[PDB]
Amino acid sequence: AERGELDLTGAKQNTGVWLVKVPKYLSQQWAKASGRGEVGKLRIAKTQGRTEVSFTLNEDLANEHPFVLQSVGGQTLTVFTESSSDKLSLEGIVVQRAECRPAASENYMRLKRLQIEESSKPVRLSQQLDKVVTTNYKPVANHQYNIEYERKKKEDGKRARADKQHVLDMLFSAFEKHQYYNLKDLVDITKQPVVYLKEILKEIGVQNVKGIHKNTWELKPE
Amino acid sequence: IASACLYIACRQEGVPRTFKEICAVSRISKKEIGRCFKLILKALETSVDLITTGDFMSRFCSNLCLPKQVQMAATHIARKAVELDLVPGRSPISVAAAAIYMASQASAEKRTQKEIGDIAGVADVTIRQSYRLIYPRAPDLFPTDFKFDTPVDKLPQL
DNA sequence: AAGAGAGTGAGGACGAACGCGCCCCCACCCCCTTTTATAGCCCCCCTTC
DNA sequence: GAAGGGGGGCTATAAAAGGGGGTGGGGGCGCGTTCGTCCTCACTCTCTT
Picture 1 (cartoon, chains in turn brown, green, blue, yellow):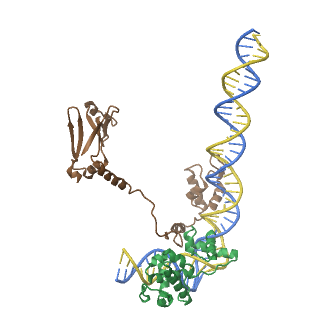
Picture 2 (cartoon, helix red, strand yellow):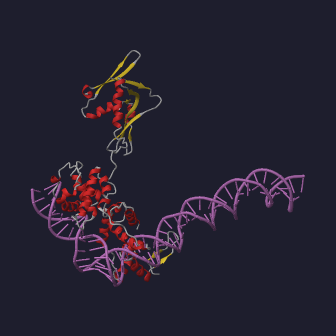
Picture 3 (cartoon, chains in turn blue, cyan, orange, brown):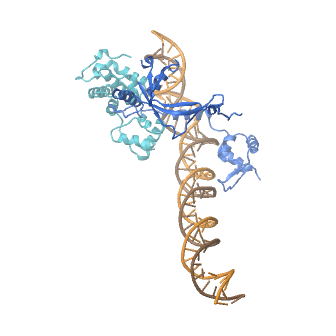
């Protein structure tokens, strides 16, 4: 007994179930209400040496479905369900397979044609355009992306030259986090001018040639 | 440099495009194109003939789906307004847009102030200012052989 | 007169070389700001209906 | 909520200041392929036996 255990009780009882193939319109009508608890009646008629299966559509639902059985000896089928509470169980074993066919032949294709046309609605096609489009590349003093970027840079402003002591303290404090830093990445952390930062870094720090990516600055002066 | 050169090339060929039109096709702002435009002229020691109101009537009217008669009237109105000095100091593009608006309002094909501004690249406020200056002399500016769908006396006032 | 080792022909895996980039660093320029008159153009915000 | 008007901003123009940031031109070396050197093996002679 565990979460992954399968409740194989249905197999023990050898419960039999029927697998039925039905078209979409029959199920679509059921899916319309799908909560009235009734969609039709399944009638089975048996004779001395012949059995026939047929289904009748509900009168309210509409506002004959002959059934053909199929051999199940070529493949063994079982039905299982997964409970929302993580408790899998086996409903039973399929004992017969059936298929549903339309009683009508001529006007039935008309319903199918509507479905094919209906499923063709998302099929987009190129549209002829009477007048050439004149709304593209409209005159503009400056692009929106450009002024927004320009405004951001102006608001942020240029980086200022902080005192050497404060810059040095920040550099040494950040050195503990990682052994080595990239010049570009170090600039963001220190937020100082590249030329000014390089001069400070040169005064104490040095760059070591690394054969894996490239020569990078090392915060350790020695 | 290329965007400014494209602007000069259009001027030198007699089919000027306004700085906004060139900017709309380039990542470079209109301000920078003008800066390079003046530098190029100094470097090349060349010059470009001053643009006129009629240099944009064909493109603007065609882009506005206006008939030929409206374009002819719009060209006549803009030239006459400049000749009469009704809009001294106004940019030719502003006058052209206002002239198009006056002619458009006087025909079956009527274009709003916003529509002309978008194609002309001129703010509707600017079109309003230029139109207000030429509105008083509307009967004189319109061509003599022009059919008014809306009478000149009933042109929009604003 | 007969064994291991070898010559030769011949097939299969590996290292140095050759490119072939992608990233970087160093000149060079531009931009920032301030002042002022000018006029047109344009944008944000307020107000009227 | 649509539309007009008021106030405010952008642009060029010169000129100087000092310095951050962007960009173009060279320089630097890591990693995916390619060929010759190296190494392994099947089928016959030879020195030693």
